[PDB]
Length: 244
Ligand SMILES: O=c1[nH]c(=O)c2ncn([C@@H]3O[C@H](CO)[C@@H](O)[C@H]3O)c2[nH]1
Image: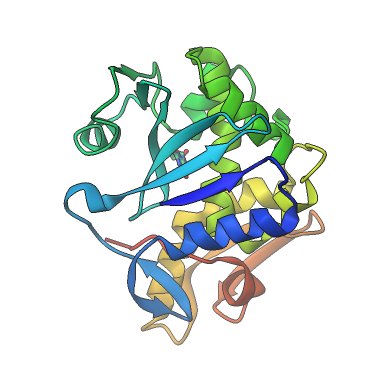
């Protein structure tokens, strides 16, 4: 398992949590020095448990699919909660079985669906460590509207930070003051599957992307990613979604 305590959290302890989270995701090989997530894992081993604690020490446990860093659901006190999608019902077979009742949220984990349920897009929801404090508090007691926004914060401050060093650094900047994600943050979240695909394909194409990827850079400017010498590949992306 991995844990993160917001009580006494600083940029250093958040960075240690994101390091713990990346290290709990298995890999057999690296492609261009980036861990390649497994095509599949059978049984309960597919799901990593993250123990998150708000400033007041109240906690949820979050289930993460280790093949794709997708959050499936979470445990709050004696109630489990899962997204309304087949991958999450499958996860409910292995995690939080001991919960008194299992609620299926009235949405899938898709960003588009969560934003409709929350009533705001990601671009207008402040993220940071205070926002994660608020998200954990929201999730402790069922409220499906409130939970959709809390889940957008949770996804970005855990899974997306694991996937991209730049997003980890953006949340560190927001240790004590929330701020809507940067344009590069949204760009990277949107592009992880594409980048993962082009980096795997670049093996057999001399490190050249078969299809270049349009991103927004750290200064808010367009950058076209054509090959593995790009700083997005050499410094930023930390995990690859297996092309399978
Ligand atoms: O639960 C989630 N964890 C994630 O890391 C994550 N990243 C993206 N999503 C969104 O969920 C959809 C899959 O059902 C994707 O299309 C993303 O929008 C995520 N959902």
